[PDB]
Length: 240
Length: 11
Ligand SMILES: CCC(CC)(c1ccc(OCCCC(=O)NO)cc1)c1nc(C)c(CC[C@H](O)C(C)(C)C)s1
Image 1 (cartoon, each protein chain N blue to C red):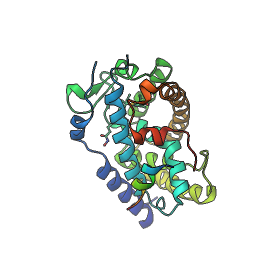
Image 2: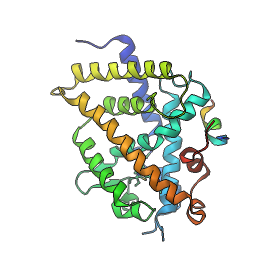
Image 3: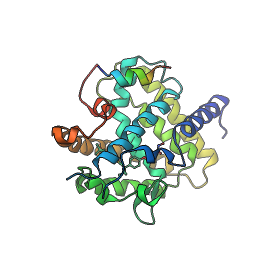
Image 4: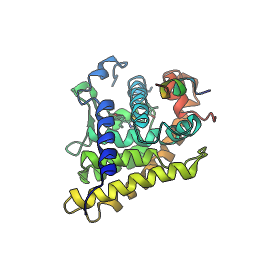
């Protein structure tokens, strides 16, 4: 009924990695192409997502064991999971009070209608919002939020990964940390671990729907030209 | 291929 030295180190590493790659001031948003409220929100949200991918990559590189993987496995894990990590880390700015994502000022407050003006439909956005409120209602500790992100990223069951056994062993270590953390440090958390694993399963369904809608978007050059080179690379279909 | 990812993954 106690966390080990190695488990505590892993938590401290992941929390620090998250603080180093998540800006609570949202001060970089003013450097994106501005919001316009045709797909009027596509430039701004493309820039937001591009920025997010960079942060997700920076977080990944500080996950214990991630940098020891092959470059090909690191890419394979990021290409498959980046959209899910973005959905997870967007939960911090999500607000139950008006079902929107508030990133600083009123200009960087996004509702469902804003994302439809970037090319997405309710078939993605309705489950996405229901995902966000259910995740928000979990009231995760920071430690649990960063562990769930790292567990999602280190999933061996993605297309293109080669060292399934090494990646699974890393993910297993993180799950054991999460389970022990909820046991010792999260009061009334009897069913919390199972609820978090279920959230990882919801994310695969969101991933699938977003990929469908991203393909439809990015096959039209008048829209793909509004994306960034990083978005095109990471969400694209090239294989190593 | 993956020009930007490879770069960003270096340090
Ligand atoms: C709906 C929520 C929202 C947009 C408002 C979101 C994303 C990231 C957020 O990041 C929080 C703050 C980061 C930070 O501060 N990092 O440090 C906050 C909110 C998105 N969700 C998804 C799945 C999106 C897919 C984009 C799409 O595919 C195209 C751009 C190609 C059209 S856009």
